[PDB]
Amino acid sequence: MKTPLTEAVSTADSQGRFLSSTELQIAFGRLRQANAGLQAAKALTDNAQSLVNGAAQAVYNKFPYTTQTQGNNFAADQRGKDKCARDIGYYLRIVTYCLVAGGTGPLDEYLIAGIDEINRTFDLSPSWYVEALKYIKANHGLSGDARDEANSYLDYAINALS
Amino acid sequence: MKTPLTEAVSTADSQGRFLSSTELQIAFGRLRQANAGLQAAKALTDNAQSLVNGAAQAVYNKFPYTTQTQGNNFAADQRGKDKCARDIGYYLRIVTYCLVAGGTGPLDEYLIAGIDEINRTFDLSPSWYVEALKYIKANHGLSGDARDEANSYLDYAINALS
Amino acid sequence: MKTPLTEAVSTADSQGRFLSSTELQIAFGRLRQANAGLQAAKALTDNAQSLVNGAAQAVYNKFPYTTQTQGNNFAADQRGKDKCARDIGYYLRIVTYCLVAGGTGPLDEYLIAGIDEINRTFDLSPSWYVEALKYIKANHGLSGDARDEANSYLDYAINALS
Amino acid sequence: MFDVFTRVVSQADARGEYLSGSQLDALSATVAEGNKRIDSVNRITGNASAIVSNAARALFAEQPQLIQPGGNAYTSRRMAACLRDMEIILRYVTYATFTGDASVLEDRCLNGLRETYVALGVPGASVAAGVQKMKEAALDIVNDPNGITRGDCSAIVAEIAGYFDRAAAAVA
Amino acid sequence: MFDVFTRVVSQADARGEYLSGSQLDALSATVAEGNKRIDSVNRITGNASAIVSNAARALFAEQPQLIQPGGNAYTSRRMAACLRDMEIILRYVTYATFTGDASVLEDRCLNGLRETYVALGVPGASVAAGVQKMKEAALDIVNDPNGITRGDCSAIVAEIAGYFDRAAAAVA
Amino acid sequence: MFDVFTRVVSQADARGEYLSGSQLDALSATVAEGNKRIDSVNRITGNASAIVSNAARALFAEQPQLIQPGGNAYTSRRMAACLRDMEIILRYVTYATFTGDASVLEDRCLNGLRETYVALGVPGASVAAGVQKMKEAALDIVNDPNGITRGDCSAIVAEIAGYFDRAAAAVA
Amino acid sequence: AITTAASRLGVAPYNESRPVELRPDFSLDDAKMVIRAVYRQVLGNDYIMDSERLKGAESLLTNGSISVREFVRTVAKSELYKKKFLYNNFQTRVIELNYKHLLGRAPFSEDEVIFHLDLYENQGFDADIDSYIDSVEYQENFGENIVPYYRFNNQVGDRTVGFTRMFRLYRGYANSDRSQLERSSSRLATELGQNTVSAIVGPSGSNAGWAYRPSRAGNTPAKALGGTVPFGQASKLFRVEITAISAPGYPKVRRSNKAVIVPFEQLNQTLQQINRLGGKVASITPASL
Amino acid sequence: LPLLNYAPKSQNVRVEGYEIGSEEKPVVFTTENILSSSDMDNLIEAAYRQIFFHAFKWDREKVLESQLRNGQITVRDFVRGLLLSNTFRNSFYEKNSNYRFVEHCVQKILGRDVYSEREKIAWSIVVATKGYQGLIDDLLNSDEYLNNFGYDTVPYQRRRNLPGREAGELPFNIKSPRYDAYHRRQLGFPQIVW
Ligand SMILES: *[C@@H](C)[C@H]1/C(=C/c2[nH]c(/C=C3N=C(/C=C4\NC(=O)C(CC)=C4C)C(C)=C\3CCC(=O)O)c(CCC(=O)O)c2C)NC(=O)[C@@H]1C
Ligand SMILES: *[C@@H](C)[C@H]1/C(=C/c2[nH]c(/C=C3N=C(/C=C4\NC(=O)C(CC)=C4C)C(C)=C\3CCC(=O)O)c(CCC(=O)O)c2C)NC(=O)[C@@H]1C
Ligand SMILES: *[C@H](C)[C@H]1/C(=C/c2[nH]c(/C=C3N=C(/C=C4\NC(=O)C(CC)=C4C)C(C)=C\3CCC(=O)O)c(CCC(=O)O)c2C)NC(=O)[C@@H]1C
Ligand SMILES: *[C@H](C)[C@H]1/C(=C/c2[nH]c(/C=C3N=C(/C=C4\NC(=O)C(CC)=C4C)C(C)=C\3CCC(=O)O)c(CCC(=O)O)c2C)NC(=O)[C@@H]1C
Ligand SMILES: *[C@H](C)[C@H]1/C(=C/c2[nH]c(/C=C3N=C(/C=C4\NC(=O)C(CC)=C4C)C(C)=C\3CCC(=O)O)c(CCC(=O)O)c2C)NC(=O)[C@@H]1C
Ligand SMILES: *[C@H](C)[C@H]1/C(=C/c2[nH]c(/C=C3N=C(/C=C4\NC(=O)C(CC)=C4C)C(C)=C\3CCC(=O)O)c(CCC(=O)O)c2C)NC(=O)[C@@H]1C
Ligand SMILES: *[C@H](C)[C@H]1/C(=C/c2[nH]c(/C=C3N=C(/C=C4\NC(=O)C(CC)=C4C)C(C)=C\3CCC(=O)O)c(CCC(=O)O)c2C)NC(=O)[C@@H]1C
Ligand SMILES: *[C@H](C)[C@H]1/C(=C/c2[nH]c(/C=C3N=C(/C=C4\NC(=O)C(CC)=C4C)C(C)=C\3CCC(=O)O)c(CCC(=O)O)c2C)NC(=O)[C@@H]1C
Ligand SMILES: *[C@H](C)[C@H]1/C(=C/c2[nH]c(/C=C3N=C(/C=C4\NC(=O)C(CC)=C4C)C(C)=C\3CCC(=O)O)c(CCC(=O)O)c2C)NC(=O)[C@@H]1C
Ligand SMILES: *[C@H](C)[C@H]1/C(=C/c2[nH]c(/C=C3N=C(/C=C4\NC(=O)C(CC)=C4C)C(C)=C\3CCC(=O)O)c(CCC(=O)O)c2C)NC(=O)[C@@H]1C
Ligand SMILES: *[C@H](C)[C@H]1/C(=C/c2[nH]c(/C=C3N=C(/C=C4\NC(=O)C(CC)=C4C)C(C)=C\3CCC(=O)O)c(CCC(=O)O)c2C)NC(=O)[C@@H]1C
Ligand SMILES: *[C@H](C)[C@H]1/C(=C/c2[nH]c(/C=C3N=C(/C=C4\NC(=O)C(CC)=C4C)C(C)=C\3CCC(=O)O)c(CCC(=O)O)c2C)NC(=O)[C@@H]1C
Ligand SMILES: *[C@H](C)[C@H]1/C(=C/c2[nH]c(/C=C3N=C(/C=C4\NC(=O)C(CC)=C4C)C(C)=C\3CCC(=O)O)c(CCC(=O)O)c2C)NC(=O)[C@@H]1C
C-alpha cells in the first residue's frame, strides 16, 4: 500500500540497508503534508453526503439516458440510483483514506485493482464515474495543499478510468 | 546516486507508474532539507584545511606507531603523511557531496563501496579513519539540521568502517 | 517381540533399572538354549518342503471336502492348493523364527495377532491348520531340547487356534 | 542516475574539488524553484491520459496512413502498443522533470530506442511527431494560470520542453 | 505492510466508514510526534555498529558456552552469522519505529524466525538475550539528552521498547 | 526393540525366507561369545556410578562454562538432570550390549533426544563429550584382565564402542 | 496397529508396554510401578525431583486409601502439575496437554476446546481436570485401576485427525512436553480452528527432517489447486516439506523451513537441489489427484 | 546429446561488483516478504515487465496470478508459467529464429546477455530436441538462475549499471524488442510516410 513511509522502508529493505537521511527526508516530507491531508479528509467527510448526491446528479445530468433507460446497469429505478450513489460514495470515502495515508495506497488496494473487470462485467461506463469525480473536484471547496493532494487522488482515479 | 529524488523515481519506475503524491512528498522533504545541506557543505568546505589537518593529527596522536613505524602502510615519512592527509581530505570532500546530494549516494559510490578490499589489501587500519571521522564530527561546529544531516553521513561512514 | 533378551530389557527399562543378576540369569538361560534352537531351525529348514507338502496332504486327507468343494476358501483348484501350501509354509517358516529368537515373538508379531479375523473374514477353518501343525510335530524328527522347544511353539500355535 | 544536485557532484568529484560558492548558490536557486518543479510534475501527471489520447488523436488525423489497414498503428495490439509507448515517453519526461536531470530519461527510455523502432519497423519520425504534440499540450497544462499561486514558470517550462525535444530527437 | 496511518485506514475500510473525528485527531497527535520519531530512528541508526558489537560482546561474556569450541557461535562463519542476525533484528526494529507499526517487523523479520533457529540448532533463548542487550543500549542512546532539542520522548521510547520486546519473544 | 537374534529374523521375514546356513552359523558364533557379553554388561553395570560421576567431573573441568552461573548445568535441578542424562545413556548402552543390537538405543534413548536438547538449549556437543568420557572409562573397565577368566574380548569391546559412538553422534 | 513405522515414529516402546494395572490386594512393588507410571504419563516425562514428589498422595495410593484414578486426579490437581502445565501456558495449550496426559490422545475438534475453556473459565482448573477423569472416555479406557497410556492404535470412537495430531503432541520417547521445539505454543490452535491436519514428522534421531515447522504466515497449501497447469507438462504433483536450509545463506536464504509443490518429473531435480541447499526432507505427500 | 561447448566472455556479472544498494540496484521482488495484495500486484507487474516488457489485458494470466497469490506456486513457477504462456510463445518464439529466441530467454531468465553466437547456437537446438518446455526448465533449473534468483525472487537484468556512471548497458527490453528485422520484413515494415 503505497505511502511515503512504507515506500521508504520497502526501498531500504530491498537494499538490505538501515534507513538513511534519504528516508528521513521522506518522513519529513510526509510530516509536511500530514495535517493538510487530515484536514482535507475531515472536510470531505463532513461534506460527504452533499458531494455524493451532487456528484450523482451531475452524472445523471451529463448522461440523461442513465436515468431513462431500463436495465440492470442503469439508474432508471431507485435500485440503480442507490447503486450509483453507493459507488460514488466508495470513491469519495477511499479518496479520504488516501488523504489520511498520504498516498494512493487505499485507491490501489481497495478500488483501482479490478475496476476494469467490474465495469466491463456489469456494463458500467467509466465515463460516468469520471464525471462524478470531476464534480467532486469542482465542489469540495478545499484550498492550498489540501486541494492539491485531494485533486491528485481524484485525478489518479480519473486517469485509471481513462 | 542515492538521493531522495533518485530513489523516488526508482520506486515509481520499478512499478511502471507515474510519480504520485507519495513521490511529490519526497521532493518536499528534499526541499525542506536542501538549504541546510548546502549551508553545511559551505561550512565544511571553508574549514576544510583545518578539519583535515586537525583530523590527521588526532589520528597520529591516537595511534603514534603510525608516525614511527617504517612501512608503506604507515606515515613515518612525508610520503605516508601525504597519503594520509589525502585520504582524510577525500572523506571530508565526499561528505560535503552527501550534504549537497541529500543522500549517502556520493559516499556509497566514491568511497564506501570496496573500501574493505582497499584497507585489507594495503594494510590500512579502519580504526585510523574512524578516529579522523570522530574528529571532524567534534570539530565542524554545525548546528541544527546541518549538524544532524552532516553527522548522519559521518556516522554512516564510521559504521561502514566497523 | 517376546524373547528372553528383549523382555529382560523391556522390564528393566520400565523399572528404570540397570540390568542386574536377574537379567544376567535370563541371558544364561538363553545361552543354554540357543544352540539347540539354532539346530532345530536348521533341521526344519532343510526339511521344509517335505514337511509343508506332507502337512498339506495330512490336511487334505483329514478334511477331504477341502479338495472337492468349489469356493474361494477351499483347495479344490490349483489356486486354492497354492494358497494352502503357502499358508502352511508361513506357519513352518515363522516357527523356525521362534526357534532362532528363543520365544514366541515371531509367531505373535507375524502370525497369531489378527489370525482370528483373517480366518473369519476368509472363511478358513482353524481346524485345518491344527492338523497341519500336528503333522509337523509328528514328522520333524527332532529330539531333546530341540524337540521340546520346537513342540512348544507348534503347540503355542495350536492353542492359539483352539 | 543523476538528479540536478548529483549532476554537479559528479563533475566536482571528477575534478577532486569541493563545490564552489557559485555552484552552491546555483543549487540554492534550484531549491527556490522546487515548488514550481513539483507543480509542473503534478500537472502533467494529472492530465497524462488526456495528453496521450489527444496527441494520439491528432497524430492519426494528420498521418492517416498509420491507422489504415497495413499501417503500423492498425490492429488493436499495434494501436495499443503505440498508445502505451507515448505514455512511456511522457512518464520518463516527468521523471526527468522531477529529478531536474535528463539521465534517467536517456538511460531508461531513450538510449537505444531509435534502434528498437528500426528493428520493429515503427516509423520513428511519426513517433517524434506524436511526442511534439504531447509537448505542446503538456506545456499548456503546466502554464495554465488558473487555480495556483501566480508566478513565473518560464524556466521550468523551458526545461520540460527540452526533455520533450530530447525525446523527439532520440526516437527518429 | 502497514504504517501508523494505513493501519487505521485498513480498519476503517473493513467497516465501510470514514475515519471518525477522534481518529483523525489521534493521527494528528501522531504527526506532532513525527520529529521525535525521526530522531530516535536516526540515533539508533547512527550507533548501529556499536549497539550490535557491544551487545554481542556482553552476550558472549555472560554466555561463554556460545563461543567455546562446539558452541553455536564458535567458528568464524557462525560468529559472523550471529553478528549479522543481531544487526538484522535491530534494522527491522528501526523500520517498525520509522513506520509506527509492527507489521514490517512481524512480516519480514519475525515470521518463521523461531522455526529457522530451531531447525539450525541456534539457541533462541540466547538470541533473545542479545536482543535484550541491544534494547537496553538502544533506549539509552535514544533517551540521551545531549545535543538535541529538549522534550519528552517517553511515548516513542515505550513504542521502541515494545518492538524490541516482540523481537525477543519471537526468536524463542 | 530387536535383539541380535530377532534382528536377523525380521530381515528374513521381510524377504519371506528361512535363515540360511551361514546366518545360523553366525548366530552360533554369537552364542559362543555369550559369556563375554554378560561379563561386559556386568562390569559396566557394577561400576555405573563411578563411570557417570568421573565422566561428569572431567567434563565440567574441561568445560567450566557449563557449571558457572547461567551455564546449562548450573543450579541443582539442571545439574541433577544432567547427571540423570549421563546415567540413562550409559544404562541404554548396557541394554544394547546385553541384547546385541542398537535398536533399544535407537528406539528409546536417542528417539527425540536431539529435539529435547535443542528445545531446552542443552549443548549437545557437550553431551557428546561426556558420552565419550564414559566410553573411555567403560572400555577400560571391560578390558581389565584382573579377576576374570582370561580371553580376547576385542570383538565385544568394539561393539560396545559403537554403541557409545551412536549415542554421541545422536546429540552432536 | 503400527508395525513397520513404529520405531521411526517413536511408537515401538509403547507397542512393547502393557497397561499398568493396580490389582486388588496389590503388592508394594505394584504400587511403586503405578507411581512411576503415573509420574511419567501425567507429568509428560519430565524429570521429577525428590523435592517435587507428592509423598502424601503416594502414601495414600500405597495404602489403598485412593485408587489409581484418584491418584491420577491428585497429581493432575497438584501445584506440581499446574506449575509445569498451567501457569505459563495459553489455555488451549493446557487443554492439549490435559488430553495427552489424562486421556492419552490429542483433541479431535474445536468443540473440545470450547467445552474445556468455558469449564475452566466458569468453574476453575480443578473442575476442568475432573471433567477429563470423570469422562466416559476415561472410564472406558482406564477405569478405576489402570494408569493412562498413549492410545496410538485405532479404537472405536476415534477420528483420523486424532492420529495425525498425536505426533504434534508426542515428539519421541527421550522427550518431554516441556522440551519440544514449539516450547509453550499451542500445537493445535490452528488445526482445531480450521479443522485441518499436518503431515506427520516423526521424532529426531530416526527422522532427519524432524525439525520441520511451518511459519506463522506465507506457507504453502496442502493441495495443488490448479493442478499441473502452472508446471506445464506434468503427471502428478507432490508437496515436499524441507527443513534446515542453510547453504546459500542470508539473504538468499530467509526461512530455513520451506514447503514446495513440485511435479513428478522434477523430483530428481528437487532432491538434488534440496541436498545442495543442505536441507533435509521432512515429508513428501501427493498434492494432486 | 550434451550441449555444444562454448567459452564465456568477460561480463560484469562474471566478477565481484562490491555492490551497495542505490537507485540502480534492481528492486528485489520476493514472496519471502509476506507481501500484501497491493504489494503482490507490484511483484506480478515486475514479472510481466521482466518477461513480456508489457502485458496488455489480453496477455495477462489471472489464474497463474491467483495461484502465486495463494502460495500454490513459487515466483520461479510463475516465471515458468509466463514463459510457457501463449503471449511468450507468440511474441518471442514464433516471431524469431531459434537463435534469437535463445537470446531472449537468456536475457529474460538469467538476467545477462549471451556470451556469443556460439552460446546462442548451442542452445538453439534444445527446443527441437528436448521440446519447448525442456529449454525453459534447463534454464530455470540452472545453477546460474538458482544462485541469483532462487525460487522466490523475480529475475532482473544484472549489474547493468556501474557506480558513478551516467548510463549503464542498454535495458534488454530496449536492446531486444520482441521481434527484429526478420519478422519486420514479413509484416512489410518500415512504412513509407510523408
Ligand atoms: C527523543 C527522541 C529526544 C528528543 C527529540 C526531539 N527532537 C525534536 C525536534 C527536531 N528534531 C529534528 C530532527 C532532524 N532534523 C534534521 O535535519 C534531521 C537529519 C535528516 C533530523 C534527524 C527536527 C527537524 C526537529 C524540529 C526542529 C527542532 O530542531 O526542534 C524535538 C522537539 C519537538 C518536536 O520537534 O516536535 C524533540 C523533543 N528530545 C529529547 O530530549 C530526547 C532525548
Ligand atoms: C572381556 C569381557 C573379559 C573376559 C571375559 C570372559 N568371561 C569368560 C567366562 C565366563 N564369565 C562368566 C560370567 C559370569 N558367571 C556368573 O555366574 C555371572 C554372575 C551372574 C557372570 C557374569 C561365566 C559364567 C563364564 C564361563 C565360565 C568361566 O568361568 O570361564 C571368558 C572365557 C571364555 C568364555 O566365553 O567362556 C572370558 C574371556 N575375559 C578377559 O580376559 C576380558 C578382560
Ligand atoms: C508553474 C508552471 C505554475 C505555478 C507554480 C507555482 N507554485 C507555487 C507554490 C507552491 N506550489 C505548491 C504545491 C503543492 N503543495 C502541495 O501540498 C502539493 C501536493 C502534494 C503540491 C503539488 C506549494 C507547496 C507551494 C508553496 C506554497 C504556496 O501555496 O504557494 C508558486 C509560488 C512560488 C513558490 O515557489 O512557492 C508557483 C509560481 N504558478 C504559475 O502561475 C504557473 C502556471
Ligand atoms: C460505432 C459502433 C461507435 C463509435 C466509433 C468510433 N470509433 C472511433 C475510433 C477508433 N475505433 C478504433 C477501433 C479499431 N481500430 C482497429 O485497428 C481495430 C481492429 C482491427 C478496431 C476495432 C480505434 C483504434 C479508434 C481510435 C483510432 C482511430 O481513430 O482510428 C471513433 C472516434 C474516436 C476519437 O476520439 O476520434 C468513433 C466515433 N462511436 C460511436 O458513437 C458509435 C456508436
Ligand atoms: C505510436 C506513437 C507509434 C507506434 C508505436 C509502436 N511501438 C511498438 C512496439 C514497441 N515499443 C517498444 C518500446 C520500448 N521498450 C522499452 O523498454 C522502452 C523504454 C521503457 C520503450 C519505449 C517495444 C520494446 C516494442 C515492442 C514490444 C511490445 O510491443 O510489447 C509497436 C508495436 C510493434 C509490435 O508489434 O511489436 C508500435 C505500433 N507505432 C506507430 O505507428 C506510431 C507512430
Ligand atoms: C591476538 C593476536 C590479538 C588480540 C586478540 C583478541 N581477539 C578477540 C576476540 C575475538 N577473536 C575472535 C576470533 C575467532 N573466533 C573464532 O571462532 C575463530 C575461528 C575458529 C577465530 C579466529 C573472535 C570471534 C572474537 C570475538 C568474540 C570472542 O570474544 O570470542 C579479542 C577481544 C575483543 C573484544 O572486544 O572482546 C582480543 C583481545 N588482541 C590483541 O591486541 C592481540 C594483538
Ligand atoms: C564445602 C562446604 C565442602 C566441599 C565442596 C565441594 N563441592 C564440590 C562440587 C560441587 N558442588 C556443587 C554444588 C552446587 N552446584 C550448584 O549449581 C549449586 C546450586 C546453585 C550448588 C549448591 C556441585 C553441583 C558440585 C559438582 C560439580 C561442580 O564441581 O561444580 C566439590 C568438588 C567435587 C568433585 O568431585 O569435584 C567440593 C570439594 N568439599 C569439602 O570438603 C568442603 C567441606
Ligand atoms: C549433562 C551431561 C548435560 C545436560 C543435561 C540436561 N538434560 C536436561 C533435560 C532432559 N534430559 C532428558 C533426557 C532423557 N529423558 C528420558 O526419559 C531419556 C531416556 C529415554 C532421556 C535420554 C529429557 C527428556 C530432559 C527434559 C525433561 C526434564 O525434566 O528436564 C537438562 C535440564 C534442562 C533444564 O532444566 O532446563 C539438562 C541440564 N546439560 C548440560 O549442560 C550437560 C552438557
Ligand atoms: C487395506 C485395504 C490396506 C492397508 C491398510 C492398513 N491400515 C493400517 C493402519 C491404520 N489404519 C488406520 C486408519 C484409520 N484410523 C481411524 O481412526 C480411521 C477412521 C475412524 C481410519 C480410516 C490407522 C489410524 C492405522 C494405524 C493405527 C492402527 O492400525 O491401530 C495398517 C497397518 C499399519 C502398520 O501395521 O504399520 C494397514 C495394513 N494396507 C494395505 O496394504 C492395504 C492396501
Ligand atoms: C469479542 C470482543 C470478540 C469475539 C470473540 C470470540 N472469541 C471466540 C473464541 C475463542 N476465544 C478464545 C480465547 C482464549 N482462549 C484462551 O486460552 C485465552 C486466554 C486464557 C483466551 C482469551 C478461544 C481459544 C476461542 C475458541 C473457543 C471458543 O469458541 O470459545 C469466539 C467464537 C468464534 C467461533 O467461531 O466460535 C468469539 C466470537 N468475536 C468478535 O466478533 C468480537 C470482536
Ligand atoms: C547470534 C546472537 C546467535 C546466533 C546466530 C546464528 N544464525 C545463524 C543462521 C541464520 N540466521 C538466519 C536469520 C534470518 N533470516 C531472515 O530472513 C531473517 C529476518 C529477515 C533472519 C534474522 C538464517 C536464515 C540463517 C541461516 C543462513 C545463514 O547462515 O546465513 C547461524 C549459523 C547457523 C549454522 O548452523 O551455520 C548462527 C550462528 N547463534 C548463536 O549462538 C547466537 C545466540
Ligand atoms: C587495474 C590494474 C586497472 C583497472 C581495472 C578496472 N577494471 C574495471 C572493471 C571491470 N573489469 C572487468 C574484468 C573482467 N570480467 C571478467 O569476466 C574477467 C575474467 C573473469 C575479467 C578480468 C569487468 C567485467 C569490469 C566491469 C565490472 C566491474 O567493474 O565490477 C574497473 C572499473 C571500471 C569502472 O568504471 O568502475 C577498473 C578500475 N583500472 C585501472 O586504472 C588499472 C590500469
Ligand atoms: C465468488 C462467487 C465468491 C468469492 C470469491 C473469491 N475467491 C477469492 C480468492 C481465491 N479464489 C481462488 C480460486 C482459484 N484459483 C485457481 O487457480 C483456481 C483453480 C484453477 C481456483 C478455483 C484462489 C486460489 C484464491 C486465492 C488467491 C487469489 O486471491 O486469487 C477471493 C479473494 C479473497 C482474498 O482477497 O483474500 C474471493 C472474493 N468471494 C465471495 O464472497 C463469493 C461467494
Image: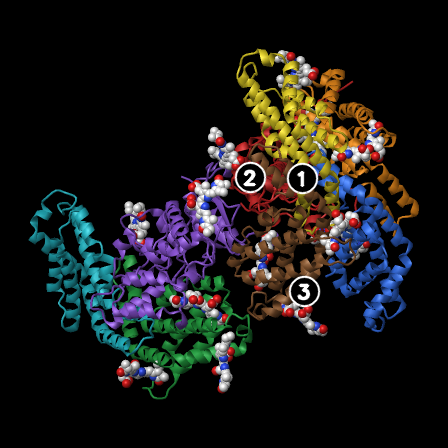
Chain colours: A yellow, B blue, C cyan, D orange, E brown, F green, G purple, H red
Is residue F65 shown to the viewer in this render? yes
Write the residue at 25% across / 72% down: G28
The picture quadrant where one finds residue D87 is: top right
Spatial CA distance of label 3 from label 2 is: 44 Å
Disc 1 and disc 2 in contact, CB within 8 angstroms:
no
Where does the C terminus of chain H fall, quadrant-wise? top right
Residue pointed to by mark 3: E54
Residue found at x 84% / y 66% = B58
Q: Chain of mark 2?
A: H
Ligand 13 near label 2 (Cβ, under 8 Å)? no
Q: Please give the label number shown on residue H78.
A: 2
Q: Which structural element holds mark 2?
A: helix
For residue A89, which quarter of the picture? top right
Q: Which of the four quarters of the rendered structure image does ligand 2 lie in?
A: bottom left
Label 1, on which residue?
E25
The span from disc 1 to disc 2 (Cα, nearest Å) is 44 Å
C61 in relation to C33, above or below? above
